[PDB]
Amino acid sequence: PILLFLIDTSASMNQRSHLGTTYLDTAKGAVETFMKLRARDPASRGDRYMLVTFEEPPYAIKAGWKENHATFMNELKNLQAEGLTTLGQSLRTAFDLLNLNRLVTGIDNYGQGRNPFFLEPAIIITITDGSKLTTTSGVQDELHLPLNSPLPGSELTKEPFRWDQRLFALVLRLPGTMSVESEQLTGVPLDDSAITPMCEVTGGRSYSVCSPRMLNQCLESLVQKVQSGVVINFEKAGPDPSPVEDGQPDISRPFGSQPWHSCHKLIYVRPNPKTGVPIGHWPVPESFWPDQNSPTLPPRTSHPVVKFSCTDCEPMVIDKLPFDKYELEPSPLTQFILERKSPQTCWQVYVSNSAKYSELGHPFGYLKASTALNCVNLFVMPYNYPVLLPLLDDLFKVHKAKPTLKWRQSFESYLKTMPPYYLGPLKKAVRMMGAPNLIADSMEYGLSYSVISYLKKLSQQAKIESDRVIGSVGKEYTGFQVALLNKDLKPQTFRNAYDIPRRNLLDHLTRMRSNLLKSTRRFLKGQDEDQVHSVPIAQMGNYQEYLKQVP
Amino acid sequence: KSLQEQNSHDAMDSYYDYIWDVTILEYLTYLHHKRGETDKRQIAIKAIGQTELNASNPEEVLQLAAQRRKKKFLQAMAKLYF
Image 1 (cartoon, rainbow over the protein chains, first blue to last red):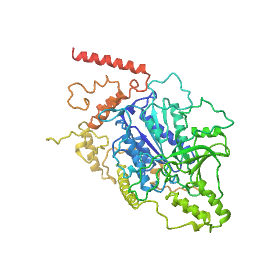
Image 2 (image 1 turned 60 degrees about the vertical axis):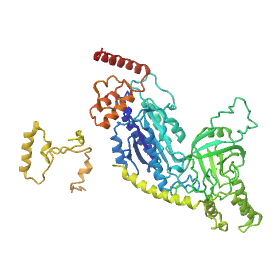
Image 3 (image 1 turned 45 degrees about the horizontal axis):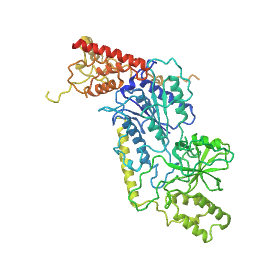
Image 4 (image 1 turned 120 degrees about the horizontal axis):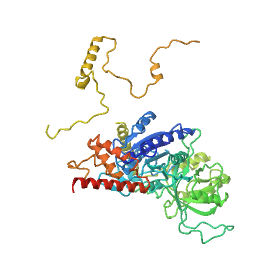
């Protein structure tokens, strides 16, 4: 996946803990230990590391797509916390980088549905301290991201983040004096910071740390959550949960505020074992009926809102029709359903405003308890599966391709009720079915000409902006300014007479004379050229001849 | 707004001992880094890096350090004027 670290480089991050070290050094150590614990996992060969600091552009992206691991280390160890607490601009810059390359590659197919197989997994971790949000004018009470629309195409999604990326926050609260009381909580508390509502919206969690042991627990938990998936918002709608006849309905059950109403939670996307890209079949549908004459598509939600109905049904699993199935990671919905203990019943998940005539949506999937009752899976079929699947059953039971008449009228009714972007996969569906006669090239349109032209032009501006951003990373009267001392000056004492101090001048003069009277094979322009950072045995031992095999 | 100006007739660095808010020291470090003060910046870093003015200390320690600095600053003003 993509691991991005947003390291706070405000001056408030220069406080010193009880360990005798600064907060920023603790952040660097957290990044290092995250590296070690992630490298312990035998699945992290491909993991792109990125770093963003709290510094104004273009000095904002320390490491991006075109850098490597060594430059990430060098820029990590050379961070100075000398800025303000400007969280919104830095978060927008990180999301702009990630969504910029996202819209460059066309990973998110607007208009053609939402395909959670096209996935670029990404976890961003903001390590900060929880101080007051500061600008050049004053303290800001509540965290607002800027809305300047720098990336072309930002108006087609309401939120600056996406459904393939997750935000976590390490808020350092190490006290100056160590606490006499020892923390014994197994779980990590949430903080009362200004970043916590944002990470709860994006489908993450804010780890609050007050001790180095607590930092170890937080960072182990953060390592355990770096996997590939899609965060979707599950909500119920309409009927109440069905009371079991064996169960007893009680007034004490809360009918107004129940913990699994809404959950922005993850579903798992396993890679393809043979290739890596999960070869998928069915999209999660849109929140609008596609008007093929509208000039612009409506802006899409960053996180899909899917409504589940708890009415018990029968899980229809037809042979040789490829459905797609996900595992949904633990959530109060999942512990409820695992308490229900009914692997013969499923709940019906649908997407609202996906029907031409009804505000309610015809069901597109079902959530289902597994055989071993270890996890709750999500099964997705094409749109309106209880209509489509029995007729496919009937064609491979009786009709043998060339069909009857009423069943033709059933498919004309179905394709009038069918979404047009689903016209993509369903055609591909019969390419596995064994009935290519249902393929008709007459209908292939899913979008208007205007939005396709807009998408092409947006892709072109995205390519230009990607080139710009990748080139940006890694880089006596009223006109008088007194020069400041430069640490990276390298004062060359042999190239220039101006750089020799007085108190050793005669000394250096004699040395200079010796150079011009040495007449050696190699002439040096510096008195002391020791090294820069590292003195390796292997690097210098390669520049010699060692003719001793000794066998 | 006051710290942004460049015509102070009182001391700059020797009054940095009577500050106990991390936010104002944060702004001081930012101003000194922008405007070229490479030495007042280090004074601000030393002030922030004290184990007495951390934000996450127990409240008694913070309020007692605050009242110590209040006493010393008000005595310094009574030294100058009064």
